[PDB]
Length: 274
Ligand SMILES: [Zn+2]
Image (cartoon, rainbow, N blue to C red):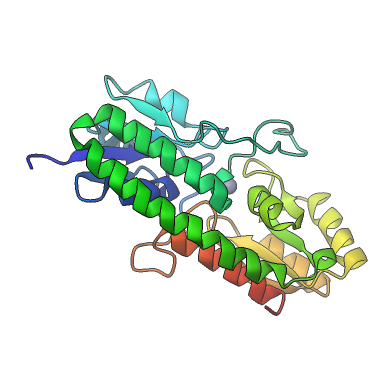
């Protein structure tokens, strides 16, 4: 066991999934730090250093990292793999990014199984000496992710179908909303320039009042102020922050992808009174 294979990912969700497949034979690090906004991140010379010292770079694609392709042109002789191949996208519904793929595919546990398979294939391709370890680790982790779906689905099924309205800040939850049958309301369709402008707030306030939606949420990498404004003006409670674009730190309450899905579903369910 000389030097461990080095994997660099664009953001923290992929870091944790890949580290579970890598186990003990590779070290996986994320370019972005926990809590950092990932869509419009501005890479630094230090990020270039980290990616250039890697043996493999993983990214989401599907229009998530607006910075990645320009950044990756600075990197020489390091293979890359997009980890969303074979996932059917949901289009963004409005705004300047309307009609392109919504990038947040990992919020569906069923899609996470495809993430796992793509990361496994990339590790086996570029570090074939450890293929048996990657294959064994991916099979074990896929078992855990597959078993995750049923209790989450049952928990959210307790909310009456007509009341399944998921009101968030970024429209980052479209794939979870599809899996578990939620209608989707948001202050902006994808992180970008305008987040919480008028027009956006007014529309969301209208749907909340018409449908008596009981709760609204923010997310961990963006400002909670628009969501709290919406809850102040309506009958909805502020349900707290959901985790989608980033894990917490390792010593925080959302250290893993499994903990992210669990925490987000639990926070939604609590917002609806379980
Ligand atoms: Zn996002």
